[PDB]
Image: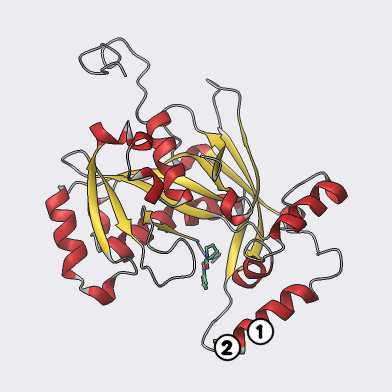
Protein backbone atom coordinates (compact mmCIF):
# COMPACT_ATOMS: atom_id res chain seq x y z
CA UNK A 1 0.00 0.00 0.00
CA UNK A 2 2.32 2.77 -1.23
CA UNK A 3 -0.55 5.32 -1.02
CA UNK A 4 -0.63 5.18 2.88
CA UNK A 5 2.26 5.66 5.42
CA UNK A 6 1.85 5.42 9.26
CA UNK A 7 3.27 8.49 11.05
CA UNK A 8 2.12 7.42 14.60
CA UNK A 9 0.88 4.12 16.22
CA UNK A 10 -0.52 4.86 19.74
CA UNK A 11 0.25 2.64 22.76
CA UNK A 12 -2.12 1.14 25.35
CA UNK A 13 -4.87 0.28 22.83
CA UNK A 14 -5.26 4.03 22.00
CA UNK A 15 -4.95 7.38 23.85
CA UNK A 16 -7.81 9.27 25.52
CA UNK A 17 -8.18 13.09 25.28
CA UNK A 18 -6.66 13.74 28.79
CA UNK A 19 -3.28 12.15 27.73
CA UNK A 20 -2.65 14.48 24.70
CA UNK A 21 -1.02 17.95 24.58
CA UNK A 22 -1.14 20.35 21.56
CA UNK A 23 1.30 23.19 20.70
CA UNK A 24 -0.49 25.54 18.18
CA UNK A 25 2.27 27.93 16.88
CA UNK A 26 2.96 29.98 13.68
CA UNK A 27 6.39 28.13 13.72
CA UNK A 28 4.34 25.05 12.57
CA UNK A 29 2.82 26.86 9.50
CA UNK A 30 3.59 26.21 5.82
CA UNK A 31 6.60 28.18 4.48
CA UNK A 32 5.86 30.84 1.81
CA UNK A 33 6.38 29.32 -1.75
CA UNK A 34 9.80 30.02 -3.41
CA UNK A 35 8.39 32.38 -6.11
CA UNK A 36 5.70 33.73 -3.72
CA UNK A 37 2.17 32.75 -2.61
CA UNK A 38 0.76 34.60 -5.70
CA UNK A 39 0.68 31.12 -7.39
CA UNK A 40 -1.96 30.03 -4.76
CA UNK A 41 -4.00 33.23 -5.28
CA UNK A 42 -4.00 32.66 -9.10
CA UNK A 43 -5.34 29.00 -8.78
CA UNK A 44 -8.06 30.26 -6.32
CA UNK A 45 -9.15 33.14 -8.63
CA UNK A 46 -9.46 30.70 -11.62
CA UNK A 47 -11.58 28.31 -9.47
CA UNK A 48 -13.90 31.13 -8.08
CA UNK A 49 -14.45 32.50 -11.65
CA UNK A 50 -15.92 29.04 -12.60
CA UNK A 51 -17.63 28.19 -9.22
CA UNK A 52 -18.38 31.53 -7.47
CA UNK A 53 -20.41 29.79 -4.67
CA UNK A 54 -17.18 28.23 -3.22
CA UNK A 55 -15.85 29.58 0.12
CA UNK A 56 -12.52 29.32 1.97
CA UNK A 57 -12.29 27.87 5.51
CA UNK A 58 -9.46 27.69 8.09
CA UNK A 59 -7.95 24.24 8.87
CA UNK A 60 -5.39 22.83 11.36
CA UNK A 61 -1.97 21.97 9.83
CA UNK A 62 -0.02 18.91 11.13
CA UNK A 63 3.74 19.68 11.59
CA UNK A 64 4.71 16.59 13.70
CA UNK A 65 3.59 14.30 16.58
CA UNK A 66 6.04 13.09 19.33
CA UNK A 67 5.14 10.09 21.58
CA UNK A 68 6.49 9.88 25.17
CA UNK A 69 8.72 6.93 26.16
CA UNK A 70 6.30 3.90 26.46
CA UNK A 71 5.01 3.04 29.96
CA UNK A 72 5.67 6.60 31.34
CA UNK A 73 3.35 8.64 33.62
CA UNK A 74 2.00 12.03 32.55
CA UNK A 75 1.11 13.31 29.05
CA UNK A 76 1.78 10.68 26.35
CA UNK A 77 1.66 12.67 23.04
CA UNK A 78 2.62 16.18 21.84
CA UNK A 79 0.85 17.35 18.60
CA UNK A 80 2.68 20.28 16.89
CA UNK A 81 -0.01 22.14 14.90
CA UNK A 82 -0.12 25.29 12.72
CA UNK A 83 -2.95 26.88 10.70
CA UNK A 84 -3.77 26.49 6.98
CA UNK A 85 -6.89 26.78 4.74
CA UNK A 86 -8.98 25.13 2.00
CA UNK A 87 -7.50 27.70 -0.50
CA UNK A 88 -3.90 26.83 0.48
CA UNK A 89 -4.71 23.05 0.11
CA UNK A 90 -6.05 23.63 -3.47
CA UNK A 91 -2.89 25.59 -4.39
CA UNK A 92 -0.34 23.06 -2.92
CA UNK A 93 -1.34 19.40 -2.11
CA UNK A 94 -4.04 19.33 -4.88
CA UNK A 95 -1.80 21.19 -7.48
CA UNK A 96 -0.44 19.25 -10.51
CA UNK A 97 3.02 20.51 -9.29
CA UNK A 98 2.70 19.06 -5.73
CA UNK A 99 5.66 16.58 -6.30
CA UNK A 100 7.88 19.57 -7.42
CA UNK A 101 6.93 21.40 -4.16
CA UNK A 102 7.94 18.27 -2.12
CA UNK A 103 11.41 18.12 -3.87
CA UNK A 104 11.89 21.93 -3.34
CA UNK A 105 11.06 21.57 0.40
CA UNK A 106 13.65 18.71 0.75
CA UNK A 107 16.26 20.99 -1.00
CA UNK A 108 15.53 24.30 0.86
CA UNK A 109 14.36 23.15 4.38
CA UNK A 110 15.25 19.40 4.63
CA UNK A 111 11.44 18.84 4.90
CA UNK A 112 9.38 17.34 2.03
CA UNK A 113 6.21 18.98 3.53
CA UNK A 114 7.64 22.58 4.10
CA UNK A 115 5.71 24.11 1.09
CA UNK A 116 2.49 21.98 1.57
CA UNK A 117 -0.73 23.08 3.33
CA UNK A 118 -1.14 19.57 4.93
CA UNK A 119 -4.60 20.13 6.52
CA UNK A 120 -5.30 17.62 9.36
CA UNK A 121 -8.20 15.17 8.78
CA UNK A 122 -10.07 13.03 11.34
CA UNK A 123 -11.51 9.51 10.68
CA UNK A 124 -13.16 6.81 12.81
CA UNK A 125 -13.15 3.02 13.07
CA UNK A 126 -16.79 3.05 14.32
CA UNK A 127 -17.88 -0.29 15.97
CA UNK A 128 -21.52 -1.40 16.56
CA UNK A 129 -22.92 -3.26 19.61
CA UNK A 130 -23.08 -6.50 17.45
CA UNK A 131 -19.33 -6.16 16.50
CA UNK A 132 -19.29 -4.64 12.97
CA UNK A 133 -17.30 -1.64 11.62
CA UNK A 134 -19.21 1.07 9.61
CA UNK A 135 -18.29 1.91 5.93
CA UNK A 136 -19.69 4.65 3.59
CA UNK A 137 -19.73 4.76 -0.26
CA UNK A 138 -18.49 8.03 -1.89
CA UNK A 139 -20.49 9.70 -4.74
CA UNK A 140 -19.00 8.94 -8.25
CA UNK A 141 -19.46 12.72 -9.03
CA UNK A 142 -17.12 14.32 -6.35
CA UNK A 143 -13.51 15.50 -7.16
CA UNK A 144 -11.55 13.41 -4.57
CA UNK A 145 -11.61 9.57 -4.50
CA UNK A 146 -14.88 9.30 -6.55
CA UNK A 147 -16.85 6.10 -6.05
CA UNK A 148 -14.43 4.72 -3.36
CA UNK A 149 -15.26 3.29 0.13
CA UNK A 150 -14.62 5.63 3.15
CA UNK A 151 -15.12 5.63 6.97
CA UNK A 152 -16.83 8.52 8.86
CA UNK A 153 -14.73 11.69 9.21
CA UNK A 154 -13.91 15.19 7.95
CA UNK A 155 -11.43 18.13 8.20
CA UNK A 156 -12.09 20.19 11.39
CA UNK A 157 -12.24 24.06 11.28
CA UNK A 158 -10.55 26.00 14.16
CA UNK A 159 -13.00 27.82 16.63
CA UNK A 160 -1.10 23.67 26.77
CA UNK A 161 -3.27 26.74 27.66
CA UNK A 162 -4.88 27.18 24.21
CA UNK A 163 -3.53 23.54 23.66
CA UNK A 164 -6.28 21.75 25.69
CA UNK A 165 -9.11 23.56 23.81
CA UNK A 166 -7.52 22.47 20.47
CA UNK A 167 -7.34 18.77 21.64
CA UNK A 168 -11.00 19.12 22.77
CA UNK A 169 -12.04 20.42 19.28
CA UNK A 170 -10.25 17.46 17.55
CA UNK A 171 -12.02 14.82 19.72
CA UNK A 172 -15.39 16.74 19.48
CA UNK A 173 -15.05 16.97 15.64
CA UNK A 174 -14.89 13.17 15.07
CA UNK A 175 -18.16 12.68 17.10
CA UNK A 176 -19.84 15.64 15.33
CA UNK A 177 -18.88 14.14 11.85
CA UNK A 178 -20.44 10.75 12.95
CA UNK A 179 -23.68 12.55 14.08
CA UNK A 180 -23.91 14.73 10.88
CA UNK A 181 -23.24 11.94 8.28
CA UNK A 182 -24.50 8.69 9.97
CA UNK A 183 -27.46 10.53 11.75
CA UNK A 184 -26.70 8.83 15.14
CA UNK A 185 -27.63 10.35 18.49
CA UNK A 186 -24.53 11.73 20.32
CA UNK A 187 -25.52 9.79 23.51
CA UNK A 188 -25.10 6.43 21.67
CA UNK A 189 -21.28 7.18 21.18
CA UNK A 190 -18.24 6.45 23.47
CA UNK A 191 -15.52 9.05 24.12
CA UNK A 192 -13.04 8.52 21.18
CA UNK A 193 -9.56 6.92 21.59
CA UNK A 194 -6.76 8.12 19.26
CA UNK A 195 -5.33 5.03 17.41
CA UNK A 196 -2.62 6.90 15.40
CA UNK A 197 -1.94 9.16 12.40
CA UNK A 198 -1.79 8.05 8.72
CA UNK A 199 -0.53 9.99 5.63
CA UNK A 200 -2.21 9.95 2.12
CA UNK A 201 0.72 9.82 -0.37
CA UNK A 202 -1.82 10.28 -3.27
CA UNK A 203 -2.54 13.78 -1.79
CA UNK A 204 1.20 14.79 -1.37
CA UNK A 205 1.38 13.45 2.23
CA UNK A 206 -1.51 15.22 4.04
CA UNK A 207 -2.25 13.41 7.36
CA UNK A 208 -5.42 12.23 9.21
CA UNK A 209 -5.81 11.39 12.94
CA UNK A 210 -7.62 7.98 13.17
CA UNK A 211 -9.89 7.27 16.20
CA UNK A 212 -11.80 4.27 17.64
CA UNK A 213 -15.45 5.00 18.64
CA UNK A 214 -17.98 2.44 20.01
CA UNK A 215 -21.76 2.76 19.44
CA UNK A 216 -24.43 1.22 21.74
CA UNK A 217 -26.72 0.55 18.67
CA UNK A 218 -26.66 -2.62 16.52
CA UNK A 219 -25.78 -2.58 12.77
CA UNK A 220 -29.56 -2.81 11.96
CA UNK A 221 -30.30 0.22 14.21
CA UNK A 222 -27.35 2.26 12.70
CA UNK A 223 -28.64 1.47 9.14
CA UNK A 224 -32.18 2.63 10.08
CA UNK A 225 -30.82 5.99 11.48
CA UNK A 226 -28.61 6.65 8.38
CA UNK A 227 -31.46 5.86 5.91
CA UNK A 228 -34.21 7.77 7.88
CA UNK A 229 -32.43 11.08 7.04
CA UNK A 230 -33.18 10.60 3.31
CA UNK A 231 -30.75 11.39 0.46
CA UNK A 232 -30.13 15.09 1.54
CA UNK A 233 -29.10 14.07 5.11
CA UNK A 234 -25.74 12.49 3.92
CA UNK A 235 -22.90 13.27 1.36
CA UNK A 236 -22.25 9.48 0.93
CA UNK A 237 -24.56 7.35 -1.33
CA UNK A 238 -24.75 4.20 0.86
CA UNK A 239 -23.77 2.55 4.21
CA UNK A 240 -22.57 -1.01 4.86
CA UNK A 241 -21.03 -3.16 7.66
CA UNK A 242 -18.11 -5.69 7.97
CA UNK A 243 -17.80 -8.03 11.00
CA UNK A 244 -14.74 -7.13 13.16
CA UNK A 245 -13.79 -10.85 12.74
CA UNK A 246 -13.36 -10.19 8.96
CA UNK A 247 -11.61 -6.73 9.24
CA UNK A 248 -8.46 -8.69 10.32
CA UNK A 249 -7.98 -9.99 6.69
CA UNK A 250 -9.52 -6.98 4.79
CA UNK A 251 -6.17 -6.23 2.95
CA UNK A 252 -6.50 -9.68 1.25
CA UNK A 253 -10.09 -8.97 -0.05
CA UNK A 254 -11.36 -7.32 -3.32
CA UNK A 255 -12.79 -4.52 -1.01
CA UNK A 256 -9.17 -3.29 -0.29
CA UNK A 257 -8.67 -1.86 -3.85
CA UNK A 258 -11.95 0.15 -3.42
CA UNK A 259 -10.89 1.83 -0.08
CA UNK A 260 -9.64 5.45 -0.20
CA UNK A 261 -6.20 6.02 1.44
CA UNK A 262 -7.45 7.60 4.74
CA UNK A 263 -9.92 4.68 5.24
CA UNK A 264 -7.02 2.20 4.63
CA UNK A 265 -5.10 4.09 7.38
CA UNK A 266 -8.08 3.73 9.82
CA UNK A 267 -8.35 -0.05 9.24
CA UNK A 268 -4.53 -0.71 9.45
CA UNK A 269 -4.42 1.22 12.77
CA UNK A 270 -7.63 -0.57 14.08
CA UNK A 271 -6.01 -3.95 13.32
CA UNK A 272 -2.63 -3.02 14.96
CA UNK A 273 -3.94 -1.13 18.05
CA UNK A 274 -7.46 -2.61 18.93
CA UNK A 275 -6.88 -6.02 17.25
CA UNK A 276 -3.50 -7.88 17.54
CA UNK A 277 -3.89 -9.13 21.19
CA UNK A 278 -0.71 -9.46 23.42
CA UNK A 279 -2.06 -11.70 26.28
CA UNK A 280 -2.37 -15.50 26.73
CA UNK A 281 -6.25 -15.70 26.68
CA UNK A 282 -6.99 -13.65 23.48
CA UNK A 283 -3.74 -14.95 21.79
CA UNK A 284 -4.81 -18.64 22.25
CA UNK A 285 -5.31 -20.43 18.84
CA UNK A 286 -9.14 -20.93 19.08
CA UNK A 287 -9.63 -17.07 19.65
CA UNK A 288 -6.73 -15.96 17.28
CA UNK A 289 -6.80 -18.53 14.47
CA UNK A 290 -3.47 -18.94 12.56
CA UNK A 291 -3.13 -17.54 8.97
O1 LIG B 1 -12.51 20.73 4.23
C1 LIG B 1 -12.81 21.15 3.11
N1 LIG B 1 -12.37 20.56 2.00
C2 LIG B 1 -11.43 19.43 2.04
C3 LIG B 1 -10.16 19.81 2.81
C4 LIG B 1 -8.83 19.24 2.31
C5 LIG B 1 -8.75 17.73 2.25
C6 LIG B 1 -9.85 17.04 1.47
N2 LIG B 1 -10.44 17.87 0.43
C7 LIG B 1 -11.19 18.96 0.61
O2 LIG B 1 -11.68 19.59 -0.33
C8 LIG B 1 -13.59 22.31 3.01
C9 LIG B 1 -13.96 23.07 1.84
C10 LIG B 1 -14.64 24.21 2.34
C11 LIG B 1 -14.79 24.08 3.71
O3 LIG B 1 -14.12 22.95 4.13
Secondary structure type for disc 2? loop
Q: Residue at x 26, y 34 (%)?
A: 246
| Colour scheme in use | secondary structure
Report the number of numbered marks: 2
Query: Which image quarter holds the C terminus?
Result: top left
> Which of the pair 173/137 is nearer the observer?
137
Marks 2 and 1 in Cβ contact (< 8 Å)? yes
- The CA distance from mark 2 to mark 1 is 7 Å
Say which quarter of the image contains residue 279: top left
Q: Which residue appears farthest toward the front when viewing the image? A: 254
Secondary structure type for disc 1? helix
Rendered position, 233 above or below 265: below
The disc placed on residue 209 is none
Q: Where does residue 11 sit, x and y in percent of width and height?
A: 48, 28
Whether residue 242 sits left or right of residue 8 in the image: it is left
Q: Residue at x 55, y 81 (%)?
A: 55
Query: What residue did someone put label 1 on?
Result: 46
Rendered position, 279 above or below 83: above
Q: Where does residue 44 sit, x and y in percent of width and height?
A: 66, 79
- Crowdedness of circle 1 by 10 Å Cα count: few (<14), some, many (20+)? few
Say which quarter of the image contains residue 177: bottom left
Query: What residue did someone put label 2 on?
Result: 50
Whether residue 104 sits left or right of residue 288 in the image: it is right
Q: Where does residue 194 sit, x and y in percent of width and height?
A: 45, 41
Q: Residue at x 13, y 54 (%)?
A: 221
- Crowdedness of circle 2 by 10 Å Cα count: few (<14), some, many (20+)? few
Rendered position, 140 above or below 277: below
Q: Where does residue 153 sit, x and y in percent of width and height?
A: 41, 57
Rendered position, 215 above or below 8: below
Q: Residue at x 25, y 64 (%)?
A: 183
Amino acid sequence: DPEVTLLLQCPGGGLPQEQIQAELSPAHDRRPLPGGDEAITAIWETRLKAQPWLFDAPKFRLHSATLAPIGSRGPQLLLRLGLTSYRDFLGTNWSSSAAWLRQQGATDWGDTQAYLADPLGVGAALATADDFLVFLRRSRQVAEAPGLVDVPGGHPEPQDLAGQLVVHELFSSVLQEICDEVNLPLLTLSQPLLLGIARNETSAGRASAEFYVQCSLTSEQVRKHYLSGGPEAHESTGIFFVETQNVRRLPETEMWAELCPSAKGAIILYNRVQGSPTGAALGSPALLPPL
